[PDB]
Image 1 (tube, rainbow over the protein chains, first blue to last red):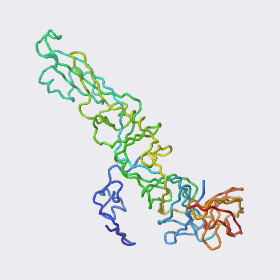
Image 2 (cartoon, rainbow over the protein chains, first blue to last red):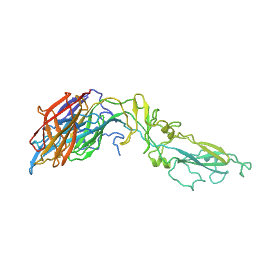
Image 3 (cartoon, rainbow over the protein chains, first blue to last red):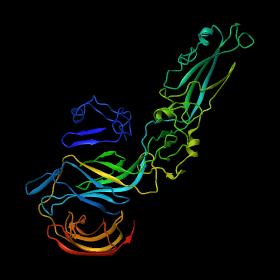
Image 4 (cartoon, rainbow over the protein chains, first blue to last red):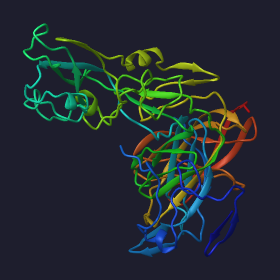
Length: 54
Length: 431
């Protein structure tokens, strides 16, 4: 799998591609565009029971 | 407590500055990387501006190394006692029919129990066919009806939160001190990130991680302590196992709310014409709680309780390395025009050289105001930054060395002009 960084460069990761978001794994909060991450779009995918509360 | 161990410097392309009102201020907007400290060591950072006296300092103190848990399936359970009601009526009395009693459901309210109420309580309704005629206590030869209204109630005034651990996360208990003086206590694990005022911080390197904790459970008690279960967790409420009747909160356990989950058919009935016996074979959680209470001995580690934070922890007897990643989200860092001169003095020196703990160096700072102390060596490799207050104060930090006979002249300053200073001491060889 590869990681794209606009303005910096590219990257490579030695692991299978993240297809399902889950806790304890790289890729639990995914989106579809750069504006969906910079502006936090509600159309993104979250994770069940991730945000903790005290 | 020891002082700062690792000391680096900020970059230039992620640190802007501005001078106005004879008060040069700077900002931080970037990402830095530094080695994490060991037990007691501090991963501190030093900032450099446009002058020599204008120098702030960030401090990040490491408490210890622990192994936190990541909960996923949590619930609440407790003890329950059955309380059934007995009310027998003959045939053709109110709502006594064979087609209705033989096909009687639990959600149907009986005619002899509708005046009680429809409260939120785990209740069920049964109807058993009994004998009739004058030989049993009726006037008709048709069988009578036995309306049974059984409801479950709480027993103990406290509940237990049974949870599990999927993957152990090596947590690093930190205590970051802000630039102004505000002290914040956070905790980083594996690659988590917390929230601070000047930005955030995340963990990079991790050399620990206990796997295979699916076949073990844990029980948390408020105020009392923790526990451990040597049995695999079950997400299905079954009989004869820890977690037969589960709920969602303490109020649902101490009051038996309808929202609680339980397995069907768990109340034994003994219909005897008039005498009604209702007994249940539930599992008491306090037996397992008092049976497997922390601390315990499991394999090669030592599981203990937590008295300070939240969640179960785990101890380990081995070294561990880590890397702290600092974040800066546009934080204003101001300075001062004129500083206050200071006078330093030598005290003692002890510790180790070329070790992860460093040497415990201490100096005697005598100043007449607040501020800091910018110092360095001769070749340009070590730095001494200690807070300077009003009066004679004793400050101690950590300085690494590569020689058992430490003897190097230092230059301390607070307002700009440096002064000579010589230190000495004997260290020990610790790997």
